[PDB]
Image (cartoon, coloured by chain):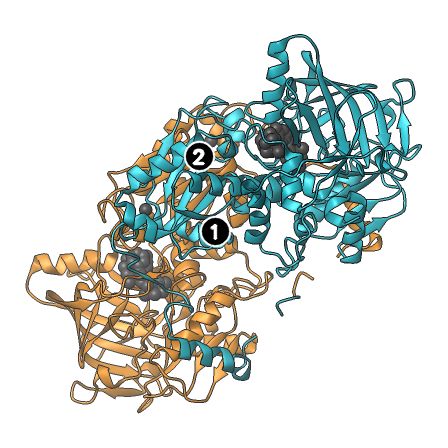
Chain colours: A cyan, B orange
Amino acid sequence: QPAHLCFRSFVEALKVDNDLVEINTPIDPNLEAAAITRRVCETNDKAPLFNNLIGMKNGLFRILGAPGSLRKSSADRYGRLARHLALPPTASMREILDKMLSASDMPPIPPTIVPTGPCKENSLDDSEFDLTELPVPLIHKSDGGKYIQTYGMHIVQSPDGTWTNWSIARAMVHDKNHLTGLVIPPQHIWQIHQMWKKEGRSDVPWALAFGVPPAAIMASSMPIPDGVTEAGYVGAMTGSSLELVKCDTNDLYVPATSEIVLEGTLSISETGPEGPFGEMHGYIFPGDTHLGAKYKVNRITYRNNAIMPMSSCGRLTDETHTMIGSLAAAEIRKLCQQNDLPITDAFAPFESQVTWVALRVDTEKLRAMKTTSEGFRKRVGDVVFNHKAGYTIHRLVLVGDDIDVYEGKDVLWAFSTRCRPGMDETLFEDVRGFPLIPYMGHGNGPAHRGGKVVSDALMPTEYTTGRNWEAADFNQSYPEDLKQKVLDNWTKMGFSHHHH
Amino acid sequence: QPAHLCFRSFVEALKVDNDLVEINTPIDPNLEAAAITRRVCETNDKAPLFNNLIGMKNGLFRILGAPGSLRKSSADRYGRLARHLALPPTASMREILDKMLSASDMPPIPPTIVPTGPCKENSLDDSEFDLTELPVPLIHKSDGGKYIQTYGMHIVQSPDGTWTNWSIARAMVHDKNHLTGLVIPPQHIWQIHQMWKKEGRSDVPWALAFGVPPAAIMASSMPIPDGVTEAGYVGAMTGSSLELVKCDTNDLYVPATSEIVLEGTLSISETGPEGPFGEMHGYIFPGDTHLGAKYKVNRITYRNNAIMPMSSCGRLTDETHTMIGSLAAAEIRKLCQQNDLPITDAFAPFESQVTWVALRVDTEKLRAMKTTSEGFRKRVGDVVFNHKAGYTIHRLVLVGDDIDVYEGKDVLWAFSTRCRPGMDETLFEDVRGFPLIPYMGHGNGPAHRGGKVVSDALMPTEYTTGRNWEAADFNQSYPEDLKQKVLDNWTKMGFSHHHH
Ligand SMILES: Cc1cc2c3c(c1C)C(C)(C)C[C@H]1C=C(c4ccccc4)[C@]4(C(=O)NC(=O)N=C4N2C[C@H](O)[C@H](O)[C@H](O)COP(=O)(O)O)N31
Ligand SMILES: Cc1cc2c3c(c1C)C(C)(C)C[C@H]1C=C(c4ccccc4)[C@]4(C(=O)NC(=O)N=C4N2C[C@H](O)[C@H](O)[C@H](O)COP(=O)(O)O)N31
Ligand SMILES: [K+]
Ligand SMILES: [K+]
Ligand SMILES: [K+]
Ligand SMILES: [K+]
Ligand SMILES: [Mn+2]
Ligand SMILES: [Mn+2]
């Protein structure tokens, strides 16, 4: 099976790419696996595959850390992400995001039901498993539980059957047969849960599939529109119908090659302690436990020699930056274009801890609008900050055509030199805020409202007659023939490879 | 003579350090020298010494580019600056700034007058030189003149004789015997000029010395207090009295080992076209010429085989970042401490194009103040933004003790995650603004007023009971013994030098 359609094949791809380290000696799921993974993510090293996890029994489980993190080289920086999508390992961020957006104006390709698959190789009923006996990692030393779920896909369906959502949301072990996790507005898992709560008749049928097709886990991390079934979006993206097998204990459908599947229910009535967890913005607040959603597990099915993917998330750079930020930025780019705004590109700078998105403006189109900074900032912020795709983003930075938004140094340059604090900004206090950012949930104001800003780093003439500067850099402040002469004589004079 | 006391010795030091490239083939001062220098600064390469400048005649002149720019290695990143100050080449930024501040609570050591020095080896009277015939560089292709003066020291004295100021301010050739340059408030050259204008009797006696003692050019770039003679500050810093020789045509005193000295007057009545120039924030606005101050040159004296230092300034990283930003930050640190504010460290992040300063707070002392963010932000901004040391800085970022302000990634992290836009900020509109920032002088508001902000990246409990988080990083979210085990087994497992 291709790497983008089968997690086991993806792990082989990373090996073949010399982007894997197999660790075959015993590693402790209590902190050690995650510490190694953390170090990998902070240094852009090879992904670790822990083949000998202390406490693995009956095939459950190995761990792959850092599945969507960065490679050291510039040339294949995003290669792990490219390997989720059948793209060359040298693919640019633009190419990755374009691939993720490509299904937005294609007909869905619905999934195909098959009778069995590798995820059915082994099973454990409700008398045979105990989630407290599995080698579930403690990811950070102050976490409030062992977070089994950092890179699996939750599957829930609307009561009427018309929408099946796939998404990533964290969850930790509560007891032998329950998890607790985050289920918060405006996320689709929460929207669907609310539908079942209003019906009031039963708990939500649920499955959680770990080690799903890589193309599926990418869509699971993207805020595609309300009501859109991720399986059909992924089908269209990849040009192939995904093969799914029915759960044993409910009528949901899981990817046939899933490494591990939990089947059960998401309660419409019960909660339990959840968190704290070392989160995407780089912090944990020890002791901050709150009630979360409660999941009951009725059955486990799994592949022979099952592998659990794990995100050891926190400070830069891991899946919470590469996937959450970039994929939200992609959706925001599309949203802006569909609202007739002249945005060509969007990216969430890693330097901003993916709390900013830089929006590149087609300034020719902006000039034709015959508008002003105040008006344009308000328009952009109204579109983005009132939409779910803008949920995680607290600062939008508008930049002109000279800025590559995929280059954080250039975004930072433009922000710092082109946006006058206060005057060139519009604050938004009556929008949904993202409580996970420390200055929100642990800050001075309402955890769930406000704290957003549009920062206009367009210069005044970009609205009127055109750019009126040249950069004071090698590229722009010297003629072509001189630049080339300098380059050609560089090593000859005495001064100091792309792949590396 | 020691490197910090003699520019010729400094050039030898850079050679000896393998931090110089001597270029002995012909190089054009029209753009080529500056393009090479620009490339050096953008790549942290070795400083270029142009020994064969097209148009050099009678000893005037060679050029040294990038005298205060960065080295590639992390271990000796700031070594060129260290070589200005007799510090080891591995000195930290903290150590460099502490050296620059050290004379602030020492008695001055006044200069010593000597009868002659190397700067008197050659002379040209007012019938013998023509500034349009010298190999003065065109630094950026759209500059409005040939900027002879990018790394020399202007010398002017108050009418009453009590204060002699040394400072860097740009100047370009106007005609055979005049320069035009920037002379703007609140700079000391401007303050002294205003004194002479109010007296109304004569033009200002002036000298401009190029290739001065390196320790002197550092103080020339620092906003030490009003009324303080830089020569005595440098004397105290270095522990030695600087040796100065009298000008021939006026009674000012110049460093004895100056490479090149211009003697003349700064007009109290005349102006001429000045600029545009590719400036510190990374921009030039072609055609934006304005009237500047006008200097008359009456005499040139110079060393045999004189060397002119040159800053090819613009985008990161050059002397306008390493010296202007860092030295302003140093002075701001001291100013805050002298106003009883609990600031331990200050730095202007390069990522901010040195328009921000991050202020590290001793949060134990802050807690004892029993204050709030609003109150503290207002206090800090009032102190800094109403002082000349704060002139160039538009955003102050307050951070707690866990943040190393000399590390831009950590400042950016703290700003992005701990300061809620709007609520955790105070805007200052009734302060002097820095017009050279594009969003000021070429922006939507007054060029000379406002546009400043204090951004509080202190978390709420930092004011009350203490930090209440741990970072989700390798350092903080794993115990010591596990961290060490991981490090010790890193290469063994299969994962990947300080000097490199
Ligand atoms: C890639 C990735 C995504 C997420 C997370 C993680 C990883 C690795 C971990 C490591 C588990 C950290 C937590 C931290 C998370 C967090 C919480 C809220 C917002 C963003 C992140 C969370 C989570 O617990 N809850 C959540 O509601 N969304 C999460 N997302 C974002 C989420 O997958 C996207 O938003 C997506 O668009 C959902 O689909 P849909 O609803 O549009 O169909 N989660
Ligand atoms: C290191 C360095 C410093 C400066 C400059 C340059 C270099 C290389 C060049 C490349 C020539 C670019 C221009 C761009 C400059 C610029 C203009 C205004 C503010 C900052 C920079 C300027 C300039 O033209 N005018 C100016 O008033 N101050 C300058 N400074 C700052 C100045 O040396 C300090 O502020 C110092 O504290 C002065 O002494 P004092 O008055 O306190 O005694 N200048
Ligand atoms: K999704
Ligand atoms: K602007
Ligand atoms: K000075
Ligand atoms: K704050
Ligand atoms: Mn969805
Ligand atoms: Mn001064």
- Residue at the right extreme of this rendering: A58
Under mark 2, the amino acid is: Val
Along the line of sight, which residue is nearer the eye, A332 or A251? A251
Name the residue: 32% across, 48% down. Answer: A366
- Residue at the top extreme of this rendering: A201
Horizontal and vertical percent position of residue A138: 77, 31
Name the residue: 52% across, 28% down. Answer: A434
Q: Chain of mark 2?
A: A
Disc 1 from disc 2: Cα separation: 17 Å
Residue A28's place in the image compared with A93, above or below, is above
- Is residue A444 something that shows in the picture? yes
User: Which residue corresponds to mark 2?
Assistant: A384
Horizontal and vertical percent position of residue A83: 70, 51
Q: Quadrant of ligand 2?
A: bottom left
Along the line of sight, which residue is nearer the eye, A188 or B298? A188
Horizontal and vertical percent position of residue B97: 46, 54
Horizontal and vertical percent position of residue A102: 57, 46
User: Which residue corresponds to mark 1?
Assistant: A405
Name the residue: 84% across, 26% down. Answer: A300
- Is residue B340 something that shows in the picture? no
